[PDB]
Amino acid sequence: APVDPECTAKVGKAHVYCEGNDVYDVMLNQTNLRDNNNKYYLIQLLEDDAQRNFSVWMRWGRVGKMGQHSLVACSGNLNKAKEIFQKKFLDKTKNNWEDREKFEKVPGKYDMLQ
DNA sequence: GCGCGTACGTGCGTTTAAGCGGTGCTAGAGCTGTCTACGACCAATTGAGCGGCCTCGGCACCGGATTCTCAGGCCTGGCGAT
Image (cartoon, rainbow, N blue to C red; front, side):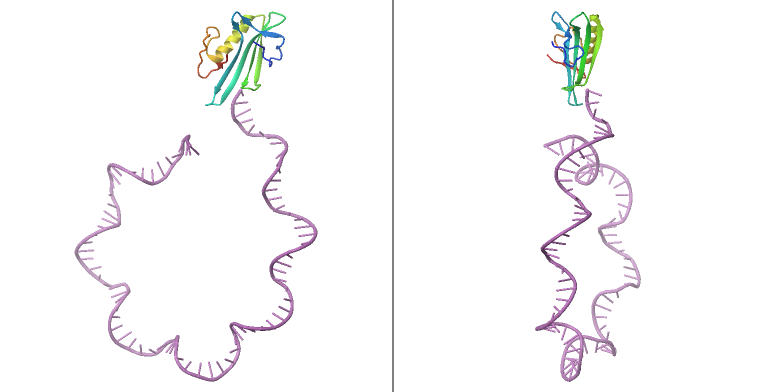
């Protein structure tokens, strides 16, 4: 699970956060020819290499384009970083992160790659 | 090949002058009669029209010069989607 190369402030200084089978790195997509949508949204919970400190990276646009981004700082509070990661995934897909081993999908919202 | 905008083809209802048969009249095409205006007939005169003759400048056109306009390019704002 690599850190986004567009995360130029934190790539090569941090890793993706993981626990047991779970991995806090996910790419969302939404494509719809009726209204000409073809877009993406990357989400990553990142932890620094040298110290127990956290951020949520996010990067989005039209598919294959640079678009926009944000690096949300969480200090030593992993629970805040988990909450922000899970909230963005929930708001973009109308369904939970945790009890979704089977990926159900709804209209007007993002899909997710494997 | 086709998205989608619309106008006339097709069915029902209203009502008006087309189509019609009788009544009635004089407007005017056609018949019969008047009579003199004028083309073609018939001839001599004579110059305009047409056949041969020039002769000159309108036109085509080759040399040289300038403007018109199509083809081959260039850059900044509108607003599209994120």
